[PDB]
Image 1 (cartoon, rainbow, N blue to C red):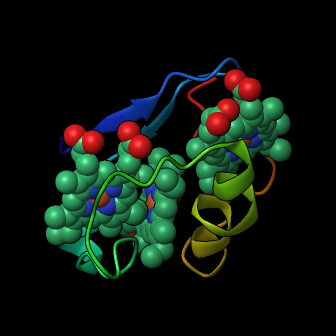
Image 2: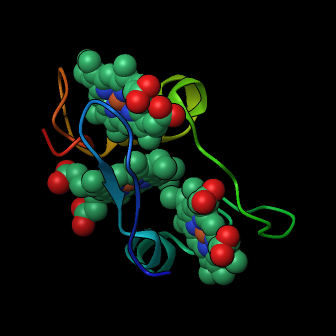
Image 3: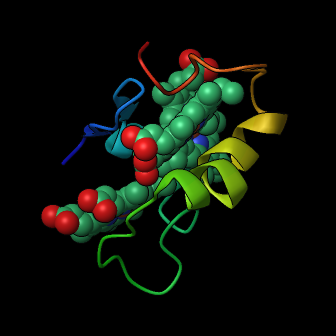
Length: 68
Ligand code: HEC
Ligand code: HEC
Ligand code: HEC
């Protein structure tokens, strides 16, 4: 899709898949080939979502992703 969300317990995490794609390229997330990714709590918080954004914008605590 162009937008997805992980409907997680906290507050659903929107991700403008398309946006990230056209803004960045593809490489950004899908090096070899896309076959899903399945970015969970661990991945997301560790080194996927909540690593990239550091140098781009400052979501300090939360809210950045979880719409809650
Ligand atoms: C990181 C911010 C991403 C960018 C940039 C792109 N994609 Fe992506 N993609 C990403 C995630 C986290 C997911 C998985 C969602 C899940 O359910 O696990 C995906 C998924 C895809 C898929 C699979 C869709 C499906 O029906 O399962 C495809 C085919 C895909 N992505 C392709 C794709 C392309 C072509 C992009 C660059 C041009 C692109 N993605 C960017 C994360 C990210
Ligand atoms: C984007 C950079 C994020 C920010 C900002 C925060 N979180 Fe997050 N979180 C994110 C994703 C993509 C996911 C995936 C959902 C999953 O469970 O795999 C998560 C997940 C969590 C979870 C687990 C929720 C569940 O349903 O089990 C927790 C407990 C969580 N996140 C907490 C949390 C808090 C407290 C934040 C501020 C400190 C926060 N998240 C920010 C993406 C992002
Ligand atoms: C680094 C290449 C990125 C990865 C990997 C992820 N995101 Fe991202 N995100 C990135 C940028 C450059 C931006 C800002 C775009 C702009 O126009 O300036 C964003 C923005 C978001 C947003 C909005 C946050 C805001 O500042 O308003 C969301 C909701 C978001 N990103 C979610 C998200 C998730 C959950 C990711 C892991 C699956 C993720 N992003 C990865 C760059 C990058």
